[PDB]
Image (cartoon, rainbow over all chains, first blue to last red; front, top):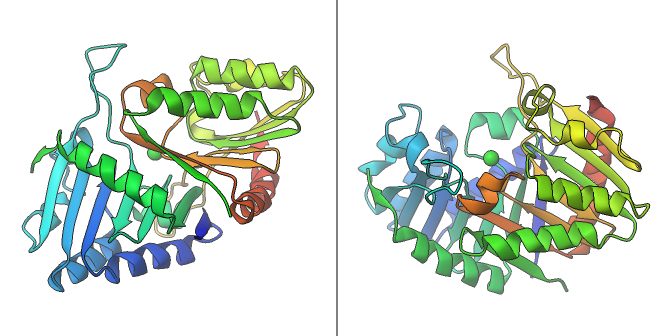
Length: 158
Length: 159
Ligand SMILES: [Cl-]
């Protein structure tokens, strides 16, 4: 097994290329959980692999994507083999507020998981300090796939 | 060979916090941190606790989030023994008159552990949010995180 760390902005070109190549070369499934997802090269890699027949699921943060014209959620909602939904975080202990869905995770087939600090935005891949980790570690992948299904429980239609 | 430990929050939020807190607390040499938002007082106390034992701690905070924020831990940790705090803004946007952010949430412990993932160091993240937190001892990842950490440290500015 291999971990491939990308430290942005230093490695921002390689990081975006790695994420786009991982989504585009999927054979079966792409499962994504993302807080913010505005980036149009990445939405086109999704659109491209869904057109090859791959099943894509995308969980977006509810508060920040349910009515947000810069989110790709509107753009991808209609798309063949592509299921998008919205997830709120848990009821808080502080106030009457709900948490956020702040993950930035992509799971490709049974083969690769991407995680780290980067939202899917031009800002993240051009202007920010960030970290993106790609891993083929099977135990990592299995746990991520298991909890992704669990999350899907609580997610709702766009 | 290495061990990835993934925590998926909120399901594993207490195990996640406890892993991170234990990783910092038991450091024997150094703690290197780059964090976007850091308001969680128990994690700050854990930093104080280990800095009190003579471990060197360095913390890069996001500049806009931390330069003037009473809920930030930067003020609480600034002049603490063995503790270096500083601020870092991102790059200028190619077609805008604004700068990026320092959005990493990373802790490097000795040469032995790196913690990375989505979670800001807040009660919000450890109590209410979906997040992921990954612990690894993979030495290639650790060396690389250390190398760029040093480069980051040369761009950060005083608090
Ligand atoms: Cl974030």
